[PDB]
Image: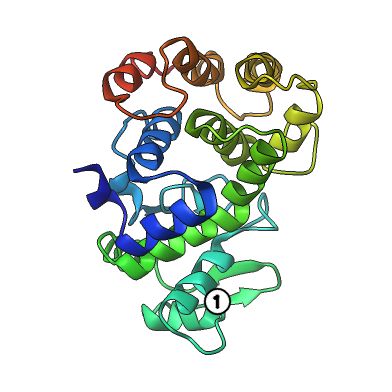
Amino acid sequence: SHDENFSPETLKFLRTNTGLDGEQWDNIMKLINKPEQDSLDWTKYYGYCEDIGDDRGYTIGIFGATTGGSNDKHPDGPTLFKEFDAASGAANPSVEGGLARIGVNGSMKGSILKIKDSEKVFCGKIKKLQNNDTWREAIWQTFYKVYIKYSVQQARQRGFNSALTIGSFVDTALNQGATGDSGTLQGILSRSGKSTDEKTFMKKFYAERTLVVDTNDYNQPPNGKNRVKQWSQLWDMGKADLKNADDAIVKVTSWKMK
């Protein structure tokens, strides 16, 4: 059952704030997970925690939140722990409160979360949260603040409300950044023109994304090209709503990752 992949509070939150239901979000996450982990099984990443050696600290959860380092001085990991404190009922949510609730030895060192626990101890503490609804809720609240809200706003200001447009935008924001430089979702949108027809606008969007998706280590070629093709192909398969789309999603994700 796809909704076992959320929590009731996450489903209500995503419905109110995105217009999409659990099937639609489950499908978006399968499509995002293919190029990130070479699997449609995104749910098993709620408790994911690894330092992959990219000088971003620890990479956590379903959307690769990071604790921070020399190549990630504005991490969203602290926001995730503060959102976990908030979800846990904290009167004055803080990073330190969220860490305190799971007994993590760490502190903010400026913009960076410095973990004093060993990799083994820290990763084990996060793994224990795999089935914790409070953690799942903090994960989605963080995902929303950093990537999804902007993605939904950009779709909605154009009169685009489809699951496939929102997921296309969220994948771009997650992979390439929401706002800032020319390669971000913001940047791609700025070059995607002014078509008021959703399918037409998105065809141009995919083409403009594809020009940069294998640059700047967003993806390794030709994985970024295949990543964008996933989203573009679902239009002619009639899956704008990402409902009853399980076979279509298996088909468009069947590419081999280099």
In terms of image quadrants, where is residue 216?
A: top right
- Residue sitting nearer the eye, 46 or 103: 46
In terms of image quadrants, where is residue 41?
A: top left
Q: Is residue 74 above or below residue 241?
A: below
Quadrant of the snapshot with the N terminus: top left
Q: Secondary structure at mark 1?
A: helix
Residue most toward the top? 236
Q: Is residue 124 above or below residue 174?
A: below
Question: Which residue is rendered at x = 64% and y = 66% of the image?
Answer: 112
Which kind of residue does numbered mark 1 sit on? Val
Residue 9 in sight in this render:
yes
Q: Estimate the x, y position of residue 92 in percent, counting from the top left.
A: 57, 88
- Residue sitting nearer the eye, 218 or 194: 194
Q: Estimate the x, y position of residue 81 in percent, counting from the top left.
A: 50, 70
- Residue sitting nearer the eye, 62 or 194: 194
Residue on which disc 1 sits:
95
Q: Is residue 166 above or below residue 84?
A: above
Q: Estimate the x, y position of residue 46 in percent, counting from the top left.
A: 35, 54
Q: Is residue 190 above or below residue 248?
A: below
Q: Estimate the x, y position of residue 231 in percent, counting from the top left.
A: 50, 21
Residue 59 in sight in this render:
no
Residue most toward the left? 1
90 sits left or right of 160 in the view: left
Question: Which residue is rendered at x = 58% and y = 68% of the image?
Answer: 113
